[PDB]
Image (cartoon, rainbow, N blue to C red; front, side, top):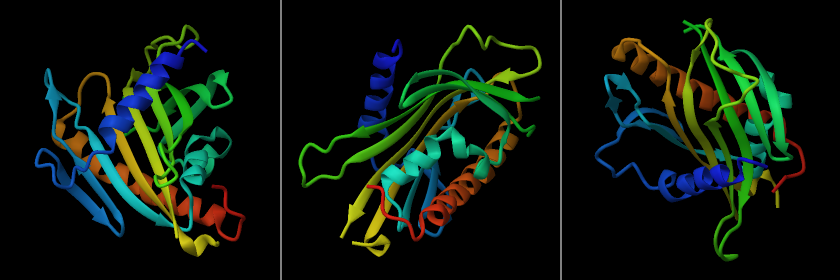
Length: 224
């Protein structure tokens, strides 16, 4: 499909930049911690607009990276875990593993987003290394979804990056998660407010989504 080079670059960007340890990085602040989940942000403004990169790490017992990424990507199950969305539809199917989604968000003016969502397995260089599953969601343009007057068009670069540690049952597997979000809404809101909402909604989402994967996979054969 036409976005293959763009997908490869975004995926490559995440594998090279998004997996670096931020725990020791002094430019990032650990803002939320609950259980095995740690949520970090870097306060960034460009031309007076809050762009705060967000990064969360998590460790989820009894699920694989493949499972987590499947549930995060698969639109067929979106409604079962998603809390912030009013409406959404698949604008175009690019490939078995790549789609374009238009969606509107619940009012927190209304935001809409138009993004390519792709799921990929990144091979390990050796059998001594873990394989990586990644879902990359990034804003694209589409002629069938132009800018409208009712919604404000957000621009996103979001990744859910998962590796599985295996030491065979669910007791013996752990999914190490890195979630990154670089989001720009359009126009204006108070910085204080945008930062308070982000601190709330991201950990809430991650906690709920990872619990959902655990619930949905328990007792089932393991999808590696």
